Length: 126
Image 1 (cartoon, rainbow, N blue to C red):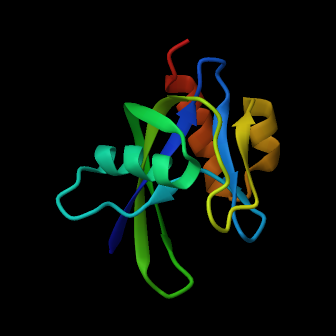
Image 2 (image 1 turned 180 degrees about the vertical axis):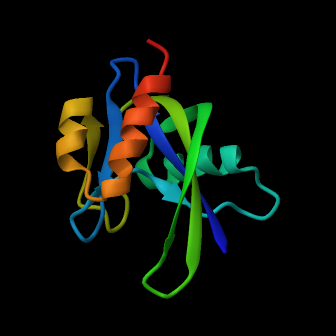
């Protein structure tokens, strides 16, 4: 299986960072860890590479699993992160921004991501 590292990033206004892929789906930023890289380090780096936002890991959430369109099993480990500043649309992306929990609940494309959002909010320091 191929591990992945992703982030549910929140700013000081308790808004979450979402990106819209080439297919028009709103999702959380995630990527592949490099050799010898901890998943936490990978999450920080992938968030920067995928959104242009500098973020830090606050706490671990939980992993999600699925089989990619090519038949490969993926297990993405998610982290609750705090970030600031405005994002930028990376190559292929069709949208990016900060959203309130209510707005995110209405935009997230993948069903499993709704649960991630709620657990992230429960653990995010008030």
